[PDB]
Length: 580
DNA sequence: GCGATCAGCGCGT
DNA sequence: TACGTGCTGATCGC
Ligand SMILES: OC[C@H]1O[C@@](CO)(O[C@H]2O[C@H](CO)[C@@H](O)[C@H](O)[C@H]2O)[C@@H](O)[C@@H]1O
Ligand SMILES: OC[C@H]1O[C@@](CO)(O[C@H]2O[C@H](CO)[C@@H](O)[C@H](O)[C@H]2O)[C@@H](O)[C@@H]1O
Ligand SMILES: [Mg+2]
Image (cartoon, rainbow, N blue to C red):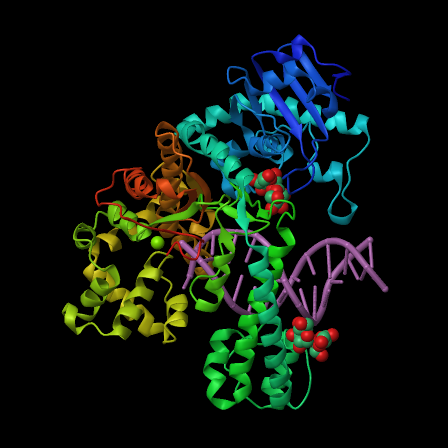
């Protein structure tokens, strides 16, 4: 049966009660400078639908939106807040965000709409968004009557579900995680996305020309060495050329055919000159297609800025993700790709990019959680952790640690964190399975606390059904009891890794909140631009660098207090690249 | 035939 | 061995 509501042609006092479920609908997936297709309000007085051009033009409604004392319950308030920021309207008073609540309760449900969250509490008097707007090419805003009922039903569900969701969060001891961490962070992420990052499109364009020329040369050389032209970017076609025409050895297969990944090509290089050329071609193409063209496609021509959207309710560990563009995977390891960062510059003249990153936060967190004596002492001495791990598992003095030993000790660390999986380890160190397990065994002997932790955490996951982070974020691990070795093992690794990655996410998130409070207190113009898992990127007047050098590291290091210190390195410069 | 999906790949922490 | 976004191609399905 249809849901009753007033489709108002004008705003009234009733719609401005001090508490309500609010819906400011933005259908475009990328909400930056996007249109708001309709508004719905549900409160003590009833249910209302307002046309955007009407409500947003009304002084009272706008004032109500920005009144922090007028409490609103919503779903994905960040989306609404940013869309409104582009319209010069401030949204305040959001005291409950159903999307974030559902996310904290169970990241695995993939809740991405009101209907999905509501289904968790057996509430189904609301339709999934996809059912209303369609999917992909056929996506479209329906006529007003259909639009209004949907928005009103969503607002109604939020109004009804607020209490049940908050009660379960309290029971999970996650209420403060929502109210004091994720919701305040949501507002900070909205300012970050709205501010955007300025881009030197001319530099990017020039790089594009050079890459295009280099790709041309290499592409011809490749056909020359192959004796024919073919689609190099086709693992299928390239496979026939390498393994059939040139007879190269098949070291690995893919469910669909021959493997041609970089790791495989590396081993094949000695056999034929075409291999190094394909590898080189892959490097250039990655830069050209994914980064140069990728960035130039989303830069706003008017401001030359890119406005990423941080998905705050997606990852199973509590990390954020970045889209359109993804600014969390910009090249840095290889010097050629690193050059791309020279294209990200300050948004104002005489301003600079400042970057601060936690040094080894995952292992410091592990030392804390496992309370491993050797590991805690290592960080208390601020030792090079990889060299120290090498010394321990290879039983040698610091002067006896060779470059290769340290490299493998690093791999073990990079691994211990992701759950002991000799297969993944052996694959990375290009060694055997047993050998990979042998290192692991040596590591636990040097760090018995870590071993006890890994055992205890897995048992705890089995007993409770989930694992938790420092700030009470949780992840359910149903496969922990699976009788399938592989499925169960993966779940055990997740049991081991989630508390580490998840707790590191909690910390930097708290740091962002703390940092913004300090910046405001100090009246600095510096502001956050990006977060990349364990590092924060800001821009500010050149005159604020010295103060930032002391303040940013301190706030990040003092976000939480662990059994070991937290260390933050920092750098600043004229471009993101120079912030090294 | 063409949009939607899958397959393989490589970039980041 | 963890967690993501999203490219070009190949294959799926209306
Ligand atoms: O607005 C971000 C918020 O919306 C969800 C769906 O409720 O994701 C949508 O927006 C993202 C950014 O444009 C897209 O990547 C995604 O495909 C689209 O469904 C949530 O996942 C997210 O928290
Ligand atoms: O020149 C375009 C034409 O060349 C082929 C090979 O016959 O593909 C080449 O060019 C593409 C565009 O950059 C690359 O993606 C591909 O790797 C390279 O071999 C044809 O597929 C294409 O129609
Ligand atoms: Mg770091």
